[PDB]
Length: 185
Ligand SMILES: C[C@H](NC(=O)C1CC1)c1cccnc1
View 1 (tube, rainbow, N blue to C red):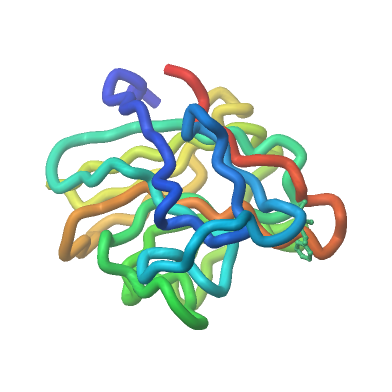
View 2 (view 1 turned 60 degrees about the vertical axis):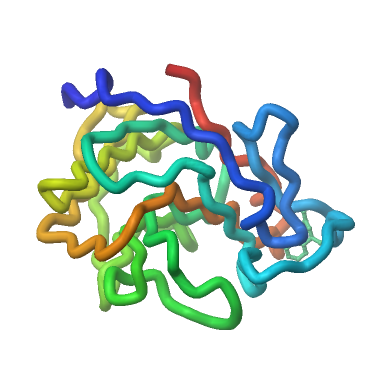
């Protein structure tokens, strides 16, 4: 692809993090802690899942960023409305304000309702995410495979400001402790 010139410097917003996450000092890496991380509760925190938002809000333009997923067995990535539900159980869908892909149990899916099987021959170690606000597009690219297209959500109805969205996943297996990292420009 040719989206690299729309690169934006994303940072994680600690206040939105599930209370078990550890965000690095530079706000560019997030991972699940061993226990709870000794923060007060607030209405912004995701309660049920190991999720966090980027600090940046987008309401126009074209934006691009990259995320490192090396070693991980499970994660969700994409964008979401600033006003998505934080508490309780919910599915990742455009109806609920999410435009996401994921890895789970050795398969890659897009967060449509119902979910859509992705066809990935080269397991990605870094994912590129492109948003065109005006066009209503969110696209995902396999950086490990020369930028090949993974998935395009088109005809998106954002209906609000967008924030970068992350889920590091649970670590019941002991094989999913590695971080999500925002990769340098
Ligand atoms: C407490 C624990 N935390 C981790 O494993 C962190 C090191 C990644 C845990 C337990 C069960 C499911 N997910 C996570």
